[PDB]
Amino acid sequence: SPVVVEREREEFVGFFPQIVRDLTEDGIGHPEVGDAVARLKEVLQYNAPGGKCNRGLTVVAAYRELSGPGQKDAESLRCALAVGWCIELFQAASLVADDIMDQSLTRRGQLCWYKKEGVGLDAINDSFLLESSVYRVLKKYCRQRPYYVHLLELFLQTAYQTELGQMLDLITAPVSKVDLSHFSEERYKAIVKYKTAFYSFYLPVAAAMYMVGIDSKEEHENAKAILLEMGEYFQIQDDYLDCFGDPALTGAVGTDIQDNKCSWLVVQCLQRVTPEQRQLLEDNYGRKEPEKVAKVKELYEAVGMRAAFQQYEESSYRRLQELIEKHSNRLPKEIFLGLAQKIYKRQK
Amino acid sequence: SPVVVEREREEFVGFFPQIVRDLTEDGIGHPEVGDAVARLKEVLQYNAPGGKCNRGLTVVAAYRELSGPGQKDAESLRCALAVGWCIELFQAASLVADDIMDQSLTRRGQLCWYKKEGVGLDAINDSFLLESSVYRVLKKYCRQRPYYVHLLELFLQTAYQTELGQMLDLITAPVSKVDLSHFSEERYKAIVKYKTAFYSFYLPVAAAMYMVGIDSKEEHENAKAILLEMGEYFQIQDDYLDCFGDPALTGAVGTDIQDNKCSWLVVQCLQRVTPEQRQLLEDNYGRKEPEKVAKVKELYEAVGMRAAFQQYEESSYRRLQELIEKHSNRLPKEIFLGLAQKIYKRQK
Ligand SMILES: CC(C)=CCC/C(C)=C/COP(=O)(O)OP(=O)(O)O
Ligand SMILES: CC(C)=CCC/C(C)=C/COP(=O)(O)OP(=O)(O)O
Ligand SMILES: [Mg+2]
Ligand SMILES: [Mg+2]
Ligand SMILES: [Mg+2]
Ligand SMILES: [Mg+2]
């Protein structure tokens, strides 16, 4: 509803300072590290606040839909909110770093933290501290809950899987080296599973699972199986929207075809090309020179990407309903649809 | 003894592959991430093995001296060994990164991992994975031990304190900017407490404490109080040995006075200088030009550093025996001396 979700929404954002407080209030005056804590306060302020905030809100939704009435107390609520910002902090730590390893300039419409003059390679240690902050907030609000160790293990494992996923990206598409050989479907796919799927979709539901007491390996697997599907599709959509989309598109209607980027668009292009294009492409992708980019898009209309999308997005939604059956046995399908309803959207 | 310690010693090093195995054996062939795991294997191999290995061996000693005969089983032993390499992995993650943020070239006589051609800023994500590896090995050998959550919390907290400590360094002495203002005793001191003291001294004993069952906040504080003393002194010694030491000195008898470095030597120099030197210094430190460095050392003989050391090292040892009393109430002073015996050494 255009009422609850935003209500859910304003509560979350209304929580941020509190978290900031948790993190630096005592540190700030500490005669020894006080200088370190202050800076964290700024590190925190610049980078954390800033997305649409979905991933975090997803904990809060699920929890609000999984818990029984015993569990809807306020503290229980606050914890949901806190574990949410925990995912938001984790992601920030990552983004901070993708940017340095990508020599990027802009993020979430502000100049990258590393580029702020005086920062530099030091953002390496600020990302760590951001990463530290997540387990600091967990100790803070859940250290005495039966699910504490599961949560710790869950944040930590997913960190490892996204990194692996980052590795694959790193090794596959260097941003100072074109090479289209490895831009392969399998690769692309495994890149997405690892680098964003787990942290963006599974992690938030899994956390509300452990919070309500569902700690069965086969149920995490049932959830895992369907959220990963979602998350794959989602990244694809994001990929389809960076080129072929525009009308009221999520703020910045920019691009990175220019950036030798492993995108679903490219990958589909590859497999569906004549050595003529396979070279026409092979040469102009990574190209920050307008003529080039423009050409790149031509090739795609030339090959008719957008329709293949519409056949994809379509296959996708079908396959979701199915796995909502085979796998939403003990859990509330209402969880997967509400999240699904805010996902498959499309633009032609 | 020149028998046990090395026996303790060869067991530890003999363990490394095993750990490597734990880390990559299944990952290596994984059809999805196999490429990511392999590289980790190399990341691991290049950076982990390489110091004298003290910090890790310290767990093993303490444990071997804290446990009762019930606990000397092999698995219990192996765990000690595993939590040891866990500290060694943690440190590697750090070193990997100090180097990038320091634009260094050499480490432990091998060229820095970041400088290996093809690596680059990507070592940012390899340090993360190294950092991930620590909690992976903990899950592996201790997930079902009553001390599991304490250990997790202990590794994680100390990570946060060393980072803070790194922050203070970062902000204090930039390696492309001299400024001697903040090279202050308090600062220097707080830098050391945080960036190396906890991880190098407290962490290893504390871990064998939690392993034997000593989880009292006041005993961790009793240990903490005396190990920090040690660790401060130790860093100082390291600092005294980079200039004024040589005879059979720990391999590389190099230097970094040349690197605008917050060292105890400099700090003592500051406080004990006439604006003449306070400028003679103010100008040639950070200097990679031989005449300069040489001058820098002059100034120190000029002010007579080495003796102030000998008065320091001396104050230090006294104050240790004392805190071994006030604070080694319930614990075995034998722990603190054997570690102490391998610490205060000196060279004039
Ligand atoms: C362990 C680490 C750092 C993981 C980073 C994960 C992540 C979300 C990468 C996305 O960035 P990207 O390379 O696709 O670029 P982007 O949105 O900036 O275009
Ligand atoms: C969170 C992080 C990265 C912490 C790093 C901690 C650490 C041991 C720094 C020492 O390096 P140094 O700056 O004194 O240089 P060195 O031995 O290389 O001379
Ligand atoms: Mg990027
Ligand atoms: Mg990237
Ligand atoms: Mg350094
Ligand atoms: Mg440094």
Image (cartoon, coloured by chain):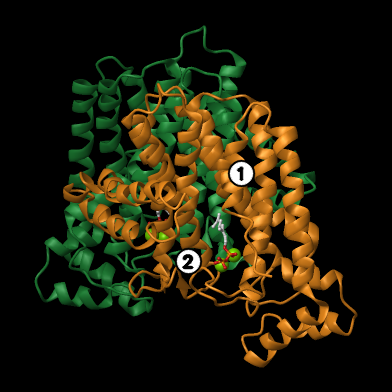
Chain colours: A orange, B green
Residue depicted at 40% across the width and 68% down the height: A113
Q: Residues within 10 Å of mark 1 (few under 14, many from 20)?
A: some
Question: Disc 2, ligand 5: is the CB inside 8 Å?
Answer: yes
Residue shown at 67% from the left, 46% from the top: A228
Q: Secondary structure at mark 1?
A: helix
Distance (Cα) linking label 1 and label 2: 52 Å
Percent position of residue A316, x then y? 74, 53
Instruction: Please name the amino acid that badge 1 sits on.
Output: Leu
* In this rendering, position of residue A52 left or right of residue A322: left
Q: Quadrant of residue A216?
A: top right
The residue indicated by pointer 1 is A337
Chain containing the residue with disc 1: A
Q: Residues within 10 Å of mark 2 (few under 14, many from 20)?
A: few
Front residue (pair A244, A194) = A244
Q: Quadrant of residue B101?
A: bottom left
* A292 w.r.t. B172: above or below: below
Q: Chain of mark 2?
A: B
Is mark 1 in CB contact (under 8 Å) with mark 2? no
Q: How far across and how far down the image is residue A105, in percent?
A: 47, 76
Classify residue B60 as left or right of residue A275: left
Asked whether the viewer can see residue B192, the reply is yes
Q: Are marks 1 and 2 on the same chain?
A: no
- Nearer to the camera, A327 or B207: A327
SS class of the residue under badge 2?
loop
Is the shortest distance between ligand 1 and the CB of mark 1 under 8 Å? no
The amino acid pointed to by label 2 is Ser
**Residue at the farthest right position:** A274
Q: Position of residue A69 (x, y in %)?
A: 41, 24
Query: What residue did someone put label 2 on?
Result: B104
